[PDB]
Image 1 (cartoon, rainbow, N blue to C red):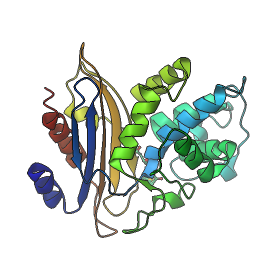
Image 2: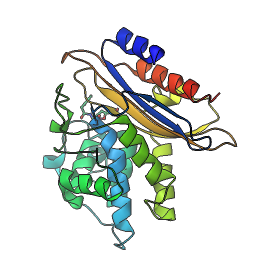
Image 3: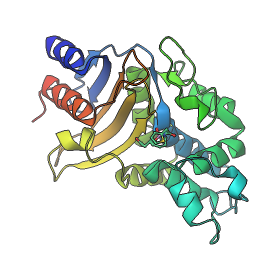
Length: 262
Ligand SMILES: *[B@@]1([O])O[C]([C]C([O])=O)[C]=[C][C][C]1[N]C(=O)[C]C1=[C][C]=[C]S1
């Protein structure tokens, strides 16, 4: 734990890490059961919830979703770009996961019954820690001591494992979820930066923009070996504290090293 302690002291905040090697059964934990803000990392689980619903509702993924300028909140690059084209549930899901599109996230939350709807999905797969309470962009406030819109690194990792590798999703939906995570564009300097270039990685990042609060979770497939699942979350005491991608990458390296994975 000393390397993690040194890392968060250099960073000037708190770091939460949980990692599991699904081959060896080994785990690494540091503040793994503390709460950290989700920021955009909830958007991965949001896409999973959509996929789960699509198992029972034919045509859900291809359903056109109506939105205009009014729905476009800051950082909606894809939904703004394709406003004229039109977007479906599936396209919004890809946008939320891979570009962290905020309007897409809100539109999908609405289809699922809001933050409460997504929280109930996570409950249904056995996640008692996850809570989403607000919409974009209020959910990014990341106030120290505030449990709203938080989870723990361990719960995040366990739920991610259930959805990508376990049986929480039917096989086709599981693979679609994996493919969306693999295609994420926002995580190249976080967990992926700690991983050898020929290992397959799927991830979703989060960046609140305040209180040094940012994160990443991932499934990593070492070549020819069983996958690793891990979560790295950070926060800091003051509103204007900067988050650090290098710190997330470093924490992921420490996690991999702790599992004895090279
Ligand atoms: B969110 O957390 O996702 C991040 C990108 C990421 O995946 O790390 C950035 C924009 C959408 C979400 N964040 C916010 O809405 C607050 C903002 C932080 C920077 C610009 S907006």
